[PDB]
Amino acid sequence: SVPSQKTYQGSYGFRLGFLHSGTAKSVTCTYSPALNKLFCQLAKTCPVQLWVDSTPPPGTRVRAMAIYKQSQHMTEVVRRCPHHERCSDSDGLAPPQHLIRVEGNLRAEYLDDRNTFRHSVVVPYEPPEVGSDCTTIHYNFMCYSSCMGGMNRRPILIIITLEDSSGNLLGRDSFEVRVCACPGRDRRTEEENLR
C-alpha cells in the first residue's frame, strides 16, 4: 500500500512552516514555496516549523515518513542506499537504514512498520515555548537523492503527520525534498525551470 499525502489541517489547524534561508551557494538548507520543495545538504540540520491554531492534547505526536513521489515507485520503501546503511554514522537512536532522522531529541522513536516495512521517526508534539509562536523540529536526511541503489535520482516527498497517542490522524502536510551538494544553486535552477 501507499501512505496518504493529502493535506489536512484538521481540528487544530496544523500546517508546516519553513525559514527563509535564501539561495546563496553556501546555503545548507533552503525551501522553495513555489515548488513546495526543500533542498538540503547531506545530514545537515533542516528546521521544519509546526504551526497550529490551537494546542492539541497532551500525548499528541509528530511523525515523518518519506515516499517516492512518482506513482510507479510509490510502493517501494524509501531507505538509505547500500553504502550509507553501512557507514556506521548512527547517532545511537536511528537505525542505520532510516533516511530521516530527528536531531537533538532524546524522545525520538524510530519505527520499522511490521506490515508495510516503511520507516518513520516520531516525536512528542511540544507546544511553543514562551515568546514563541511555533515549534521547530530539526530533521536530517541521510542519503543524497542521487545515491545509487537507494533513491537513485528518484524524487521523494516527506509526509508529516500530527497524530493522537494511538497514532490516529489529526493533521497532515508534506513537502518534496532533494538532498544534494548545492541546495542554493539547485533551488535557483529548478525555480527558473518552473518559470
Image (cartoon, rainbow, N blue to C red):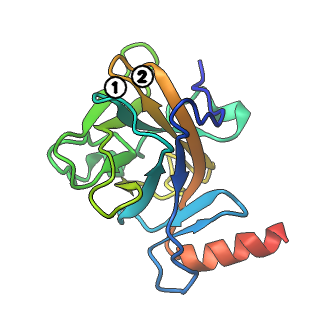
The foreground one among 102 and 84 is: 102
> Which amino acid, by three-letter code, is at mark 1?
Asp
Residue 80 x %, y %: 40, 45
At horizontal 41% and vertical 55% (from top left) the residue drawn is 134
Give the total number of marks visible in the rendering.
2
> The N terminus is located in which quarter?
top right
Q: Is residue 8 above or below residue 167?
A: below
Q: Distance between the residues labelled 2 and 1?
A: 6 Å
Number of other residues with Cα within 10 Å of mark 2, as a class: few under 14, some 14 to 19, many 20 or more = few
Q: Earlier in the sequence, mark 2 or mark 1?
A: 1
Q: Which residue is drawn at 54% across and 86% down?
A: 24
SS for dot 2: loop
For image coordinates 42% across by 22% down, the residue present is 117
Q: In which quarter of the image is the C terminus?
A: bottom right
Q: What number is the disc on residue 112?
A: 1
Q: Under tag 1, what secondary structure?
A: strand
User: In the image as oriented, which residue stretches furthest toward the right?
Assistant: 195
Which one is in front, 3 or 147?
Answer: 3
Nearest to the observer: residue 193 or residue 171 = 171
Residue 85 position by quadrant: top left
Specify the amino acid type for callout 2.
Phe
Image height of 115 relative to 26, above or below: above
x and y percentages locating residue 156 in the rendered image: 59, 46
| Left or right relative to 185: residue 70 | right
Task: Say above or below: 90 vs 62.
Answer: below
Marks 2,1: beta carbons within 8 A: yes
x 27%, y 47%: residue: 86
Q: Residue 117 carries which label?
A: 2
**Where in the figure is residue 129, as x and y percent of width and height?**
27, 56
